[PDB]
Structures are given as structure tokens and as C-alpha cells.
Image (cartoon, rainbow, N blue to C red; front, side):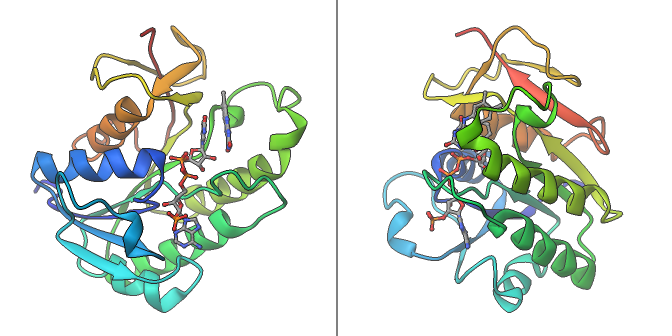
Length: 205
Ligand SMILES: NC(=O)c1ccc[n+]([C@@H]2O[C@H](COP(=O)([O-])OP(=O)(O)OC[C@H]3O[C@@H](n4cnc5c(N)ncnc54)[C@H](OP(=O)(O)O)[C@@H]3O)[C@@H](O)[C@H]2O)c1
Ligand SMILES: Cc1cc2nc3[nH]c(=O)[nH]c(=O)c3nc2cc1C
């Protein structure tokens, strides 16, 4: 049976917005959890269901995950680089809600730093990366079908659908367009080939 209903977390972020637009255009019935609905666009494709609330509130997460076939996680801290547990605590709530509701597929974005040499993280990004590592642990220990998406720098290049996906953080480049990253997260909904793996999408634009 194919995935039809999905929840997206972080849909108002850079990658989230284009993942959401692509998912709706592709035919998915999409639910989003957003703190502030004014951050969703009026033009273009629109989510089927909008839950207003916070990924740190279990009940809000629960309402969002109920009834879904799969979950996409594109949480982040925007330009905030201070020490943080928002992503990992959010993922804890998502896992609990998935288990409560029988949902078994999650595709979640962290970063290529979790594949590269772990002493090459730029200092200003260490705190966020530490929480990406906590989030990754939460998801891989959940006992759910988890695709870990670990992108390099996220750019603004056009959608191509022509990027390369490796399993080790080596690839044709150190950039992926936000649109291609979103396309890849949706690709992960229709294959099991990356379940239980870490993936590195990249492309030369
Ligand atoms: N930037 C890069 O080059 C790069 C490269 C590799 C990996 N990454 C990682 O890739 C992931 C996606 O990044 P992005 O740039 O697309 O993200 P982003 O622009 O930071 O968007 C973060 C998203 O998370 C949502 N969010 C944050 N706190 C939340 C909360 N408490 N409750 C509900 N939602 C919350 C934000 O909502 P609001 O709209 O309400 O703020 C927004 O939708 C991030 O984890 C980032 O660290 C980034
Ligand atoms: C190459 C690369 C750049 C990044 N920039 C980033 N920039 C940012 O503001 N937050 C991040 O979490 C972030 N992660 C990155 C991860 C990788 C692998």
C-alpha cells in the first residue's frame, strides 16, 4: 500500500516550504504542525490540514501524527546556534506519537556533519550538531523505519531531481538545493531502500 497521508514537521522552514509544496503537488494529503500559520504561503499548493502548536508539546504532536502513513521531519533552529534540545525533544514526541498511532515510517533531516569527520564541525555549529546527533539517536533507537537524511550545505538552486545519493557523505559536491532535498525526502516515501541507512544527497548545479 503506498504512503498517501503524511505529516511534515518544520514545514515553514526553508526546506519545509518547498517539501510541502512538492508533496501537495505530488498528490499527498499533507498535515503540518506550525507555531504560526502566517508563515505558510497563500499562493501555490496548500496543505490539506494545519495544526497550530509546538513540537515540544506532546499533545500537539499527537494530533499531527494521528492517522498518517509517514512523517517527514525538517525541524531546525533557523539562525539560532545556541545550545539546544528542540530537535531531539521534538523527535522524542514524534516517535512517541508514531508508536501511539501505528505510524512506522519517518524520514528526518539532520546534517552531513553526522557523516563527515566529527572534528571538522565549525565551532559555531557544534551545539546544533550535538542536538542533531541526539535526534539521530532517538530516531534510530525507536524501532521504526527511519531514513536519516544528512545533507551538506542547502542552497537555492532550482529543482532538478537529478542529484546523487550516497551512503557515506562522499559525493559529487557539498551542496544540495533545498528543492532537491525536499524531492529526495519525498522519494524516501516510496522506497524502503534507505530504511535504516544514512543518506547524503548532493549535486553539481
Ligand atoms: N542550512 C544549511 O545549509 C543546512 C545544511 C545541512 C543540514 N541542515 C539542517 O537541515 C534541517 C532543515 O534546515 P532548514 O534550513 O530547512 O530549516 P529552518 O529554515 O531552520 O526551519 C526550521 C523549521 O522548524 C520549525 N520549528 C522550530 N522549532 C519548532 C518548534 N518548537 N515547534 C514546531 N516547529 C518548530 C520552524 O518553524 P517556524 O517557521 O515556526 O520557525 C521551521 O519550520 C535543520 O535541522 C538544519 O540544521 C541545514
Ligand atoms: C555543509 C553543511 C553546512 C551547514 N550549515 C548550517 N547552517 C545553519 O545555520 N544551521 C545548520 O544546522 C547547518 N548545518 C550544516 C551542515 C552541513 C553538513
